[PDB]
RNA sequence: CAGGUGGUCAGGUAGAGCAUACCAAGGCGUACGAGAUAACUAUGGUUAAGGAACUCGGCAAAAUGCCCCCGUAACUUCGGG
RNA sequence: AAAUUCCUUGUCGGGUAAGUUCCGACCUGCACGAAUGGCGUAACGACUUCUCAACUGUCUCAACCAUAGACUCGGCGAAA
RNA sequence: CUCGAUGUCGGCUCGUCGCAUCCUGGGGCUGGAGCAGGUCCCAAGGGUUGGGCUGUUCGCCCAUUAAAGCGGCACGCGAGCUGGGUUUAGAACGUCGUGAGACAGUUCGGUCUCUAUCCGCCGCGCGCGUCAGAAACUUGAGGAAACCUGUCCCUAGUACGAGAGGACCGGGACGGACGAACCUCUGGUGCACCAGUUGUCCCGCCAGGGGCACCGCUGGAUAGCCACGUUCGGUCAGGAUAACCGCUGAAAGCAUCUAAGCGGGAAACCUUCUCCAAGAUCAGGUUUCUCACCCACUUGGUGGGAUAAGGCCCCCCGCAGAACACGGGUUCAAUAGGUCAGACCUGGAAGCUCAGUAAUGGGUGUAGGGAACUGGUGCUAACCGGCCGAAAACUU
């Protein structure tokens, strides 16, 4: 989606891609994850485009997601229930709830999860 | 560059009093039948019970 | 755009095959020579036994540039080489024929002879 | 009789004149303006006409400003700015509530366009004032974009006011003068002003008749 | 006009006058026209 | 679509043939040599389409006299009465910039 | 504590190689973090046209770069170059 | 006319569009000179110096991108 | 003055000032026919090039130019840069000295620290004030910025000149340099775009992909930012004037620009153009909105409480941005994201299938993928909220 304006998360752009892939995997595996608020905001459009591929559901879309995520089990979970359960919802697959900042660095924290 | 002279009390204090903590906006919430006071940005989490109230 | 210490190949038959832009004439501190700008140049190498000898300070007009030039109609002209032709103080070429294509911008700068003997004008 | 219109910069494009010449044009939607107020020399001390431009939801305007609009007897607008006129024969033609529109300007007329130039943030001295900077090499130590000297010596033991230094560029009121109006189409309230116009695509601009002609 | 701190008549028809706080000589010959400064 | 398509629409022309980078075309351009208003052909391979509607430009290249020449025209420029595709080109890039360092048979484009 | 510290072992693919790139075994993420497109500095990268015009000076950078096959000047101390 | 020449950017020639530097000479050597070696010399040089080709952000004349800082927030918290 | 340290030349960067003016502007005289000049006067608004040599300043030269001005500011400027020269320690030559050594003699090498406290400057906020509290639009006291110029054509080969040569004054066209805005074009960039590709490791394998190797490399590349790009400006007209040219006109029957008086008169000055601007504490103007209560005391231009208009903080964002500020939006919502559709970029996906021994090629199929640009969409987040914040009168 829309490229990061400013320094990318974790330092480099490559570390950015790794972070978004790993958080998308965790989000699809657990339904709900806690991360820093900037990471949650960066995840949201990335994860929703993955769900959009899952809703399309074709082998090409499978390969498109698999191009980004490496976990076969999570990609299977995506295309087996996450996509189908969002099939009748037009975008807005995720939700960010702002939670209390974490001690040690006062990093603002957020929960990101799938809508239902 | 080094300080040429020590600041006076007045000048030091005039600068130093401006180092203060930003006040957090607090609103009242009622979850689980009990009243509490939380920052406004955390109201959603407070209603979802995601905020450890201590 | 051609500036001082730029080498242009010579698109005529005066003998010079490469000249070095000395000044871009047409004003104080003028920087670049586009198509049809007049240059004073030194001949950096010429054919052996040629009319125009190495180390000669000559006047030349730029007739093709590798930097693309806008025409007023929004089109652009681009060549693969920077080339000039040595001219006399009356803007006629010192040589007797022009090699290679020539930018049409020389027509409205009154290089009419050069236009006439150019192989084809764009 | 200097004329003016409040509009929005919609971006640029090219067209071609009758002479088959390309013409870069900024299109400005000179949306209809209402007057809402006349400034008179004997009551305000100067001659001007307010112009209101831009649809806004009436709930979005505070009641001190809605009161001004309703005393003018017009629907509240989003932008409001005065066009300053000469000192005589000021309001013989502008009535509060009259709807002045793009074809107040004519084809081939010359306009002055005022806008708020695009923000540039805190800008260095090269970008902000065109300083040459320093060499990229030959020993230059960490001064490649730095201003260099900023004053003299013991005389004067200070740096003069107006010394060009780093600071915020942009967001300045800027007027470009004598821009040709290639075309005004009355069908949809847009003028095609030849050249560049200051500010964002979407920003408010005031198009006045060029007094330099 | 000759501008010198020393102005004196050159020929017999050089009128030497003082106008606007400064002295000068005016003459039929304009080469003799000459002003103190 | 774009916000300025309404300004765009009248300045466009139909009857501009479909053509792609790698195609060789004849571009007939009107040229004013005094008060003659003649038509000059420019025969060359299309090396670029740089899109955008009225602002779309296209660059075609040839080798006139030992010198490569590139002409960039606005499509929908009224200075071109019409373009004709003399051969369809088969390339696998969109901008064919490599031919500006190739001369001779090694700067050729196939016929599909 | 980005320095220093003698010796032993040291796999795979590519590679001439103990270079280098990615890996194995085996370790590690090493001890402030979280953000943020300011200037500016640093470290890298790209750059139209020109190509040393820079500068004390081509400093820095760029360029060249490998294997095989051709071919190779003045000069020479006959080895070279 | 030199790692030596003050006068001096000597003079002539070459190289450059233009050369106080460079090369070849002249000899008027302020103040060269034969083992504190003289004059040459293939090879060699992270030496000094001059030229050319190539190459380039060195420059014309800068622009943009990423990262580490700078900046903000939380913690610790100096210095001359 | 400074030795309990005031860093020395040149360059770079940034300037700023004077005018003894190089150009441009205005004039007088000329041994000024014209074109050009010479000289003097006025004039500092702007401009005043790039190279070769040298450490250089200077100077000479090359090519230009309207012109390539001269000076000051610690021979402006090293807590801004450089470090070539000079001026430590090494070494050599010449020369001097028995020598150690020495030399405004030469030669090669040899250094550039500091996190900005104060003033100063460039920007940006917070507070208060501005006789009620606010919002919008504004005046302009006073500032800032800006101020360059060429060539050609017509006038006219006319005036002038014996000819050669060759105008003034006016009008037009096109430029150079500089500046500003902008991104349509051109061009650059492009670190979540597309494609190709090398090595390797991995996804069990094939296929298809992924990690890393500078973004691995390579070809492109929308947005944004930008210049090499685009557009515009530098004007005109007034006022008061400089040098200078006068009118009327005495003292001084004449005469005289002056003594009374009145004119003309330049890029200088002031208006005019652009921008800032009421902290302009003389804190302005035109409007519009709220314009309302409650409690207590030592009853007071009293304190509180509650509010109004309004605003702030919070939230969703922005092409606005260091923070802050600014701007937009917050469900009577298209603000961001998603999503759908376009635009554009890349360039023909995967799978299947056909041809080929295969590398590969064709069909499905202008494919697939995709950021910034545009519109639709109420799916996600902008929430079930806290804090600031309103008037004695009295004089004509
Ligand atoms: Mg970006
Ligand atoms: Mg990488
Ligand atoms: Mg910005
Ligand atoms: Mg420069
Ligand atoms: Mg630079
Ligand atoms: Mg340093
Ligand atoms: Mg540096
Ligand atoms: Mg005398
Ligand atoms: Mg006078
Ligand atoms: Mg296209
Ligand atoms: Mg250690
Ligand atoms: Mg290794
Ligand atoms: Mg960080
Ligand atoms: Mg380049
Ligand atoms: Mg190039
Ligand atoms: Mg070259
Ligand atoms: Mg040089
Ligand atoms: Mg060279
Ligand atoms: Mg130089
Ligand atoms: Mg080097
Ligand atoms: Mg290199
Ligand atoms: Mg050799
Ligand atoms: Mg020597
Ligand atoms: Mg000599
Ligand atoms: Mg010699
Ligand atoms: Mg001896
Ligand atoms: Mg010896
Ligand atoms: Mg050795
Ligand atoms: Mg950065
Ligand atoms: Mg801190
Ligand atoms: Mg002391
Ligand atoms: Mg003077
Ligand atoms: Mg004169
Ligand atoms: Mg000046
Ligand atoms: Mg002025
Ligand atoms: Mg040289
Ligand atoms: Mg000066
Ligand atoms: Mg000094
Ligand atoms: Mg000086
Ligand atoms: Mg210095
Ligand atoms: Mg200093
Ligand atoms: Mg002795
Ligand atoms: Mg000494
Ligand atoms: Mg030295
Ligand atoms: Mg500092
Ligand atoms: Mg004023
Ligand atoms: Mg003041
Ligand atoms: Mg600008
Ligand atoms: Mg665009
Ligand atoms: Mg482009
Ligand atoms: Mg991708
Ligand atoms: Mg495979
Ligand atoms: Mg790995
Ligand atoms: Mg672009
Ligand atoms: Mg005037
Ligand atoms: Mg204003
Ligand atoms: Mg006020
Ligand atoms: Mg706001
Ligand atoms: Mg789409
Ligand atoms: Mg088969
Ligand atoms: Mg196929
Ligand atoms: Mg196939
Ligand atoms: Zn006389």
Image: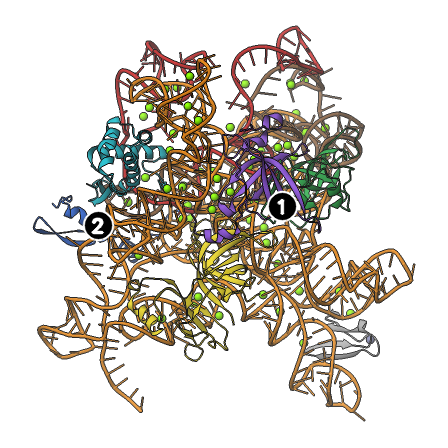
Chain colours: A cyan, B blue, C green, D yellow, F purple, G red, H brown, I orange
Name the foreground residue: C46 vs I278: C46
Q: Quarter-wise, where is residue D97 in the image?
A: bottom left
Q: Which chain letter matches label 2?
A: B
**Mark pair 2, 1: CA separation:** 59 Å
Asked whether the viewer can see residue A78, the reply is yes
Query: Considering only vertical position in the picture, is F49 above or below E36?
Result: above
Residue H46 is left or right of residue I27, and the answer is left
- What residue does disc 1 label? C31
- What residue does disc 2 label? B41
Could you tell me residue A52's position as x and y percent? 29, 37
Residue visible at 50% across and 77% down in the picture: D88
Residue visible at 50% across and 49% down in the picture: D149
Query: Considering only vertical position in the picture, is I253 above or below I172?
Result: below
Query: Considering only vertical position in the picture, is I27 above or below F95?
Result: below
Name the foreground residue: I186 vs I370: I370
Residue H49 is left or right of residue I155, and the answer is left
Between disc 2 and disc 1, the foreground one is 2
Q: Which chain letter matches label 1?
A: C
């Amino acid at each position: 989606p829309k490229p990061t304006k400013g320094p990318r998360l974790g330092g480099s752009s490559s570390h950015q891609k790794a972070i978004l892939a790993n958080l998308a995997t965790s989000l699809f595996e657990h339904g709900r994850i806690t991360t820093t608020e900037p990471k949650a905001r960066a995840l949201r459009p990335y994860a929703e485009k993955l769900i959009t591929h899952a809703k399309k559901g074709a082998l090409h879309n499978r390969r498109e997601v698999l191009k980004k995520l490496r976990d076969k089990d999570v990609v299977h979970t995506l295309f087996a229930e996450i996509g189908p359960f969002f099939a009748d919802r037009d975008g807005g697959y995720t939700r960010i709830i702002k939670i209390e900042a974490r001690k040690g660095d006062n990093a603002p924290m957020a929960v990101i999860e799938l809508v239902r | 560059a080094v300080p040429k002279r020590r600041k006076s009390r007045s000048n030091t204090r005039s600068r130093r009093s401006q180092w203060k903590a930003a006040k957090t906006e607090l609103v009242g919430v009622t979850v689980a039948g009990h009243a509490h006071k939380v920052p406004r940005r955390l109201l959603k989490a407070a209603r979802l019970g995601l905020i450890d109230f201590d | 755009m051609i500036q001082q210490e730029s080498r242009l190949k010579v698109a005529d038959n005066t003998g010079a095959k490469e000249i070095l832009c000395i000044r871009v004439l047409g004003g104080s501190s003028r920087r670049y020579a586009g198509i049809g700008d007049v240059i004073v140049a030194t001949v950096k190498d010429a054919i052996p036994g040629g009319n125009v000898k190495r180390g000669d300070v000559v006047k030349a007009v730029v007739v093709r540039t590798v930097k693309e030039r806008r025409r007023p109609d929004g089109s652009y002209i681009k060549f693969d080489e920077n080339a000039a032709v040595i001219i006399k103080p009356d803007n006629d070429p010192r040589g007797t024929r022009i090699f290679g294509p020539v930018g049409r911008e020389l027509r409205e700068k009154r290089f009419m002879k050069i236009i006439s003997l150019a192989p084809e004008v764009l | 009789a200097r004329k003016g219109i409040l509009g929005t910069k919609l971006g640029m494009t090219q067209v071609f004149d009758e002479s088959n010449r390309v013409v870069p044009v900024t299109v400005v939607k000179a949306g209809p303006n209402v007057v809402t107020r006349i400034r008179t020399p004997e009551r305000d001390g100067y001659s001007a006409v307010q112009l209101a431009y831009g649809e806004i939801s009436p709930r979005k305007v505070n009641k001190p400003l809605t009161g001004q609009y309703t005393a003018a007897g017009v629907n509240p607008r989003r932008y409001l700015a005065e066009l300053r006129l000469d000192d005589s024969d000021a309001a013989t033609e502008y009535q509060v509530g009259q709807e002045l529109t793009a074809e107040i300007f004519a084809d081939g007329s010359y306009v002055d366009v005022t806008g708020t130039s695009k923000g540039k943030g805190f800008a260095g001295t090269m970008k902000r004032h065109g300083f040459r900077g320093q060499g990229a090499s030959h020993g230059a130590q960490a001064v490649h974009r730095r201003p260099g000297s900023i004053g003299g010596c013991a005389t004067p033991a200070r740096v003069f006011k107006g010394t060009r230094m780093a600071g915020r560029m942009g967001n300045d009121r800027v007027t470009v003068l004598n821009l040709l109006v290639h075309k005004v189409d009355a069908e949809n309230g847009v003028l095609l002003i030849k050249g560049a116009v200051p500010g964002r695509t979407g920003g408010l601009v005031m198009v006045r008749s060029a007094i330099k002609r | 006009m000759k501008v010198n701190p020393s102005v004196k008549p050159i020929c017999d028809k050089c009128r030497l006058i003082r106008r606007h706080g400064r002295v000068m000589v005016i003459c039929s010959d304009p080469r003799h026209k000459q002003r103190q400064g | 679509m774009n916000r300025l398509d309404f300004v765009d629409k009248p300045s466009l022309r139909d009857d501009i043939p479909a053509f792609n980078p790698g195609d060789t075309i004849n571009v007939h351009v009107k040229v004013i040599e005094g008060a003659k208003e003649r038509l000059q052909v420019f025969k060359g391979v299309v090396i670029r389409r740089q899109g955008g509607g009225i602002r779309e430009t296209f660059t075609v290249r040839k080798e006139s006299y030992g010198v490569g020449v590139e002409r960039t025209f606005p499509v929908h420029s009224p200075n071109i009465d019409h373009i004709e595709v003399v051969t369809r080109g088969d390339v696998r890039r969109a901008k064919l910039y490599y031919l500006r360092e190739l001369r001779g048979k090694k700067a050729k484009i196939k016929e599909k």
